[PDB]
Length: 11
Length: 240
Ligand SMILES: CCC(O)(CC)COc1ccc([Si](C)(C)c2ccc(OC[C@@H](O)CCC(=O)O)c(C)c2C)c(C)c1C
Image 1 (cartoon, rainbow over the protein chains, first blue to last red):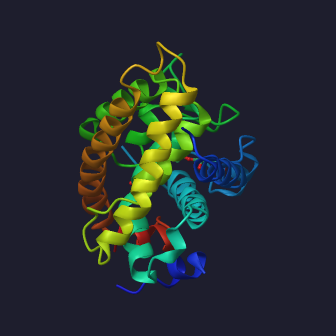
Image 2 (image 1 turned 30 degrees about the vertical axis):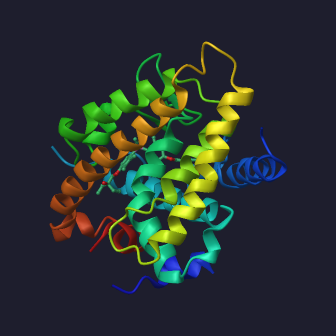
């Protein structure tokens, strides 16, 4: 489970 | 009693809420259209609505004091487990006890139990959800208490997969003492009676609503034709 969209919105 | 740091915490959270909750609901026109007039006719619209709200929850969480001192993995675990619960909490602002519906500014964006069923969900979730909304609304929370509860909900140390639970607990504890002290100093009786304990009870209610929604979401999203109607963010956060 990679969460690139969540991670990007957290950046 | 309400220290400078605690007043600062409350100011940040109020601002974060104001920056992530639009009470005009102007963006709803960007969503796929509601269909009401059996098929899950409301799933495209409500998938977009949920996905929109997940983005708002993330924007709110980022402004919680101490939240970005956590690791990326811990931030992700906390938002993945709490997003559904904060959406339920945030939705109380539009809930009206007049007809037990969520009123988002206009008839097309006014949601009742039938709309939620038309996204695939059953009374197993919907009945306790309405009971939750009624009991939360009856608390008549100050906005200060409302945004503290959303933040305490997000920074919970017992979420599955959390790594630095000691740091998550320290951040939550700072928020819990802020809320406990706010109620004791700024919420007049009789509304303040057992208010903190009632608010924590609502966090326990949210865990049960979380469990049931996750159960039904897994059932709905397991069917590819339903998953096709979801958004990429919903699939990433709620599951795939
Ligand atoms: C897609 C996954 C699903 O499981 C199908 C697979 C469906 O799930 C659903 C479907 C519908 C709902 Si509802 C009770 C109609 C809801 C949701 C979000 C809201 O928030 C908007 C707010 O954010 C606007 C303010 C701002 O941000 O500017 C509000 C206000 C309401 C009433 C819920 C809660 C879930 C979980």
